[PDB]
């Protein structure tokens, strides 16, 4: 759910993290397709090592910054994510042998802890929205979550979905409204953990109904997230995920006074084999692995199977795991875990300057290259130039490039699907129509 | 691959039969929606004639972007017709 | 008051020929016809169930509920159907 929420903040980030955690070799195919750039992106992995003596001198960040051109790697004692203003360094390089180069080469409105927003507990009836009330309300750039549930459906635990969206470094105006569309009984069963949260609304109905999806203003939503809680009851391969596929296909086909295909949607699949039904314009081979598929590469599909690789990585570097809990679900300080252990209910406390200081933690975001100071660099064709200029000017650390599928093709195309490329080389072709994954401090 | 074996691409039409006598009509309709989604995914242009145990499931399958009733697609709803 | 025989087919049974019994079995044959003539299926949906036009199908797809509106000359015009 944290990966899903981060993908909501920056589309295709769940694919980025999953490919970082999985161990993949370098593969090159001769025929020119998006798959070459994707496979170059997936080859990079997450690693950790101690910094050398050269980087422990006059100041840490200034020596750490801009040195990535000579090191040919990228850096991410405490957990540090894009720092600003013998200590571990988290590297995104490809193969651990070459990663061993930095060391060798010396030449009340918030919550009590202050991590998440908070508000007074609310009744379920207060946040229930009817079709008319949802229609009149202005919802734009918001989050809509379709939930398939019954009386016998198990608890999804949507709390882990809502915490990462409302972090302290997000201003109350910058928040994205969350609307859960689905059966009222199941949502009520999970509402008790949810009533302490702000900007949450509930709409009874079903995501298969086009009227409900029109009422919640899908055409302008920032993300639509499809979940089914009944996967544990149903065992047959065919019976699994039919509701999710139908909801995705109905959202794609829905037409507005434009086509619904351009709508960003993420679907959770328990069975990888169903992934072929998600995109109509995709070649389907059952032998093809889930990460190679177009819906996963574009970030529209997520499955928990990839998370299995975590069990390996978590063993080799314990720190890595906690960094994930920092990159998703906001921050996970031990005091917060202690309060969850004691109470299990999030509680809000009166603000103090210490809590307000604990907001410098960066957050993931999309940067548009068409409009902005980096427009000239867009057509230049050097990613490393963009990397160096961004680091020098705004100290913004860019994970990678979220790129149109058919941009490499000479003939213009109407496709809107974009795939992620992780840590592109310095000599990487750049086009103006690209997105940049970045970490930004509080403002 | 099995669709490549029976040559869906050159096939003029595809007919999906339904088990009218089933414990859960929604389950059979759902199996049929899997069939239709798979066949359209491999090939959207091909005609499909299918039996429909429930009328609202006909609405669900109408929501498919590949489904195009005007040209050559037909849905036979058993409950509606009876 | 009829001669019963399990070998006799349903179309030959006395209560079916009298129009007092119905079953979905006969509707199966529709598939064959629906393959050879697409338009004939439309005629069926016109002869029974009244007139379900593309517009009504679109409205039901969008809403799944019937809606009533104020009469206009065009709405009263399309009444010629036998
Ligand atoms: Ca590698
Ligand atoms: Ca496909």
Image (cartoon, rainbow, N blue to C red):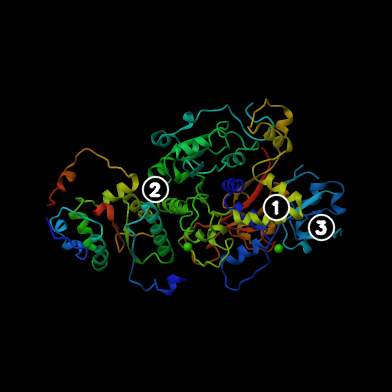
Residue A75, percent from left and from top: 75, 53
Q: Nearer the viewer, mark 1 or mark 2?
A: 2
Which callout, 3 or 1, points at the residue further toward the start of the chain? 3
The alpha-carbon separation of the residues under discs 3 and 1 comes to: 22 Å
Q: Which residue is mark 1?
A: A389
Which type of secondary structure does the marked residue at label 3 adopt? loop
In the rendered image of this protein, does residue B81 appear above or below residue A343? below
The image quadrant that residue B43 belongs to is bottom left
The alpha-carbon separation of the residues under discs 2 and 3 comes to: 53 Å
The alpha-carbon separation of the residues under discs 1 and 2 comes to: 41 Å
Ligand 1 in which quarter: bottom right
Instruction: Return the residue nearer the eye: A341 or A261.
Output: A341
Q: Are marks 3 and 1 on the same chain?
A: yes
Which type of secondary structure does the marked residue at label 1 adopt? helix
Query: Pointer 1 and pointer 2: residues touching (CB < 8 Å)?
Result: no
Ligand 1 within 8 Å of the CB at mark 3: no
A223 sits left or right of C17 in the view: right
The image quadrant that residue A97 belongs to is bottom right
Which callout, 1 or 2, points at the residue further toward the start of the chain? 2
Residue A13, percent from left and from top: 61, 52
Image disc number at residue A239: none
**What residue is at 20 percent from the left and 58 percent from the top?**
C43
Which type of secondary structure does the marked residue at label 2 adopt? loop
Callout count = 3
Q: Nearer the viewer, mark 3 or mark 1?
A: 3
Residue A16, percent from left and from top: 63, 55
Q: Which residue is mark 3?
A: A102
Give me the chain letter of mark 2.
A
Q: Which residue is mark 2?
A: A256
Residue A266 appears in the figure: yes
Quarter of the image for the C terminus of chain A: give it: top right
């Amino acid at each position: 759910l944290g990966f899903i929420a981060q993908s909501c903040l920056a589309q295709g980030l769940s694919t980025m993290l999953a490919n970082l955690f999985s161990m993949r070799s370098f593969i090159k195919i001769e025929e020119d397709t998006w798959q070459k750039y994707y496979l170059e992106g997936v080859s990079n992995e997450m690693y950790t090592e101690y910094l050398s003596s050269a980087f422990v001198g006059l100041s840490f960040p200034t020596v750490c910054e801009l040195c990535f051109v000579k090191l040919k790697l990228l850096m991410i004692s405490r957990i540090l994510i894009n720092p600003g203003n013998g200590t571990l360094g988290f590297f995104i390089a490809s193969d651990a042998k070459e990663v061993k180069r930095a060391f060798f080469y010396c030449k009340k409105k918030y919550d009590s802890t202050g991590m998440f927003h908070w508000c007074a507990p609310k009744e379920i009836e207060k946040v229930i929205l009817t079709r008319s009330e949802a229609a009149m309300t202005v919802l734009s750039g918001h989050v809509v979550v379709c939930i398939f549930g019954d009386v016998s459906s198990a608890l999804i635990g949507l709390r882990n979905l809502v915490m990462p969206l409302r972090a302290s470094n997000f201003h109350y105006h910058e928040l994205k409204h969350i609307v859960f569309v689905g059966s009222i009984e199941y949502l009520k069963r999970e509402w008790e953990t949810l009533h302490n949260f702000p900007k949450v609304s509930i709409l009874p109905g079903t995501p298969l109904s086009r009227a409900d999806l029109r009422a919640v203003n899908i055409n302008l939503c920032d993300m639509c997230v499809i979940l089914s809680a009944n996967q544990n009851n149903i065992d047959d391969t065919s019976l699994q995920d039919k509701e999710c596929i139908l909801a995705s296909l109905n959202i794609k086909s829905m037409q507005f006074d434009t086509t619904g295909v351009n709508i960003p949607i993420i679907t959770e699949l328990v069975n990888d084999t169903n992934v072929q039904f998600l995109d109509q314009d995709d070649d389907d081979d059952p032998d093809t692995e889930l990460y190679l598929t177009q819906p996963f590469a574009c970030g529209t599909a997520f499955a928990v199977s990839v998370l299995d690789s975590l069990m390996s990585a978590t063993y080799f570097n314990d720190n890595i795991l906690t960094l994930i809990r920092t990159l998703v679900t906001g921050g996970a300080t031990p005091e917060l875990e202690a309060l969850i252990a004691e109470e299990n209910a999030l509680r809000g406390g009166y603000s103090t300057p210490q809590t307000l200081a604990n907001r410098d933690r960066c957050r993931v975001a999309q940067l548009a290259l068409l409009d902005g100071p980096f427009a000239d660099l867009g057509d230049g064709g050097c990613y490393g130039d963009l990397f160096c200029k961004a680091l020098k000017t705004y100290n913004m650390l860019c994970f990678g490039i979220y790129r149109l599928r058919d941009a490499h093709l000479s003939t213009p195309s109407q496709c809107t699907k974009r795939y992620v490329i992780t840590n592109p080389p310095y000599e990487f072709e750049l086009v103006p129509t690209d997105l940049i994954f970045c970490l930004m401090q509080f403002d | 691959h099995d669709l490549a074996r029976v040559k869906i691409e050159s096939a003029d039409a595809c007919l999906i039969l339904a088990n009218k006598y089933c414990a859960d009509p929604d389950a059979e309709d759902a199996s049929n929606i899997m069939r239709v989604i798979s066949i359209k995914n491999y090939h959207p242009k091909i005609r499909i004639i299918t039996q429909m145990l429930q009328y609202h499931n006909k609405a669900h399958l109408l929501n498919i972007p590949s489904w195009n009733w005007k040209e050559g697609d037909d849905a036979i709803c058993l409950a509606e017709l009876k």
